Image (tube, rainbow, N blue to C red):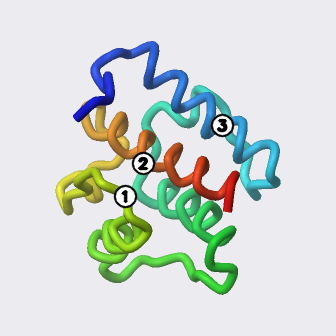
Amino acid sequence: DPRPLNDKAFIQQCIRQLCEFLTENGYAHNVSMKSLQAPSVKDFLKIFTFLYGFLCPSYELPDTKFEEEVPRIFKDLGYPFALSKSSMYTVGAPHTWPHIVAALVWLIDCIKIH
């Protein structure tokens, strides 16, 4: 894994990129650096739904089996890094969020092109 996910400054950079993309592109809810430090599973899913909607406009917010569906979508998009069920259940936890925010930023990058 080539990513410096332990570098706290690097993960603030990822969070800032998330904050800026959501803000710039008309996400429905107020977001801040503060509110993106440790999101709930429900807020993560709202964020993920907003982002994946750029690629799949009819995409609906998951809930049932989201811990299966969300990693499956990333896998299907060619994301090379592991997203475990454990991570899905604990997305906002201190040692989980860095991996998840990295995945969202990669998703943002792929939206920004395609």
Nearer the N terminus, badge 2 or badge 1?
A: 1
Mark 3 residue type: Cys
- Measure the C-alpha gap from mark 3 to mark 1: 21 Å
Tell me residue 34's x, y (percent).
58, 27
Q: Nearer the viewer, mark 2 or mark 3?
A: 2
Instruction: Residue at 42% x, 48% y: name it.
Output: 103
Task: Identify the image quadrant of the C terminus.
Answer: bottom right
Mark 2 residue type: Ala
- Measure the C-alpha gap from mark 2 to mark 3: 14 Å
Tell me residue 5's x, y (percent).
31, 26
Instruction: Residue at 45% x, 19% y: name it.
Output: 10
Instruction: Residue at 54% x, 32% y: name it.
Output: 15
Q: Which residue is mark 1?
A: 79
- Measure the C-alpha gap from mark 2 to mark 1: 8 Å
Nearer the N terminus, badge 2 or badge 3?
A: 3
Nearer the N terminus, badge 3 or badge 1?
A: 3
